[PDB]
Image 1 (tube, helix red, strand yellow):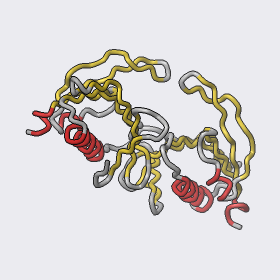
Image 2 (image 1 turned 90 degrees about the vertical axis):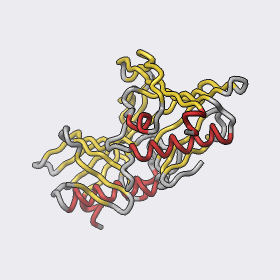
Image 3 (image 1 turned 45 degrees about the vertical axis):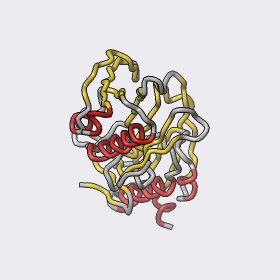
Length: 131
Length: 129
């Protein structure tokens, strides 16, 4: 069971609950999605998207990943509100171009080789998605 | 530095670093030259691969073969050594006939636990056979 876009794939990680692997069509890992909060009564899903540090721009790919996964959450899972936590290093352009709101900045939630880094909090609701 | 599926590009503005990407432009990892000695015709490098969710053996073998051709045929190197994190599958190195020359114990600290690195080697005679 997976999700397919033109250049990307999203698949559940075999051993692990709430973890999904993002790859390209040769099966090289782009990153991973981790479900952080899911509540069916609130129709609410919040996840963390890790993207490997890229040597080049992959904004078209990020846009696809987000588009693929949102379609899944909103249209195949009854979600009303989706939030996405991402390291501030990830390119914020794809999010803004797809219509996500910046809902906050989670300061100093990442420690990476001994420096604390910030995360962005993005949000989108069904109304937003479906307009 | 081009194969079928992969490419290796010298990084601008840095010394001794190469970006490994696939044809789709997605980053596989990077090569860092650690020791180069033209009088010993010796080149040792570290190759970092992002943790892969699927086996990418075929792609890693291409990357290794492309880079070996570059060192042996266009940089007059006689001996190459490659340093890799233990979490890198050894399958590409063995399948290409690299010698397993050592294990560098506890040379990596990642999220606060010690990991080893493997040391692989190939000389020209091995490459050319």
